[PDB]
Image 1 (tube, rainbow, N blue to C red):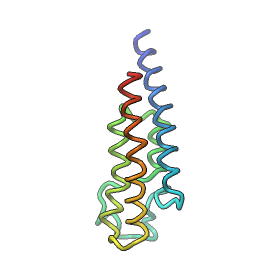
Image 2 (cartoon, rainbow, N blue to C red; image 1 turned 60 degrees about the horizontal axis):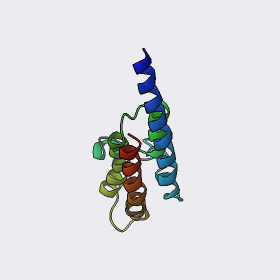
Image 3 (cartoon, helix red, strand yellow; image 1 turned 180 degrees about the vertical axis):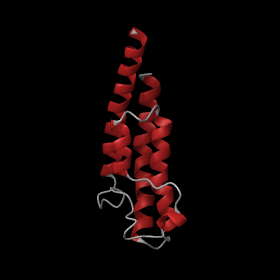
Image 4 (cartoon, rainbow, N blue to C red; image 1 turned 135 degrees about the horizontal axis):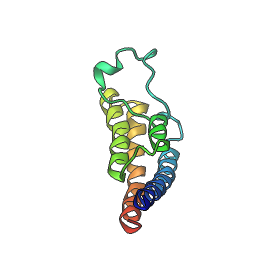
Length: 121
């Protein structure tokens, strides 16, 4: 149908906008602390602590599968990255501190993306 195509063009454009949002968020992690999944070879007890792991490569795979239906789902994944880190790592660690800075710096980017998504429909 012509409607299914119009919907698909909207998802494609959302994916395009979320890709730019992801790139801007990932720039706020220059140490690449959140780039890849926590290694289960190197932290073998991780899943006993963290039930829903997340990281930027895993978000990118979902994005390119057009697996994000709205910005809320995207934000949920970003929030997982931060919140998992802030639980597993203690306050006085480079990892915790990196998450705090990512949260604070990302807020600005997510604030505007929410306006753009509402604005452009």
